[PDB]
Length: 166
Image (cartoon, rainbow, N blue to C red; front, side, top):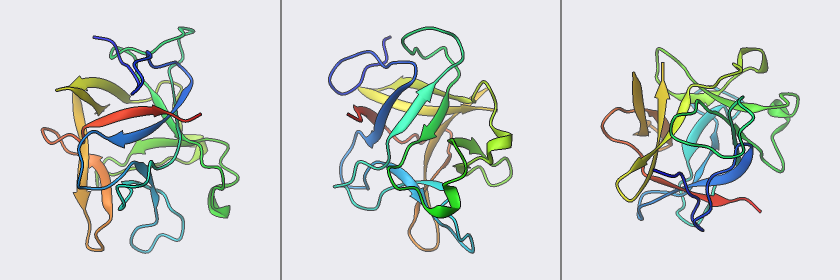
């Protein structure tokens, strides 16, 4: 199966997309939030408002191939226009999974791996994101303050689509 954006174009290696929900009524696209006692927004979350596309995400794999497929391991990097000061010296805001909490967060730059651990898979009529420590679905878990945390949640994936950032 081919990985397509919402227009029908195959996803590009190194392309930038908004990662938006395929279903209505439970939040918008993927973005960052500060959680708990953290002063910096290091958690990947779904936007509370369905009207929001979230942050552009650059998706890439080391092989010098022009398109992406479900077989490739991916790095996913948020590219905000106006990153908060605490994240301005990162260079790349790459996703990781924290092993003990299973939360998707932004990695320190020194921790980023050449091959990422994410993949994109068809899911019903849309797509899902998976994390490969076998691979497990990423889904949403609500915290005490109603933040919609992106977490490993095997069997309850967040269904997503990809919109070109432009």
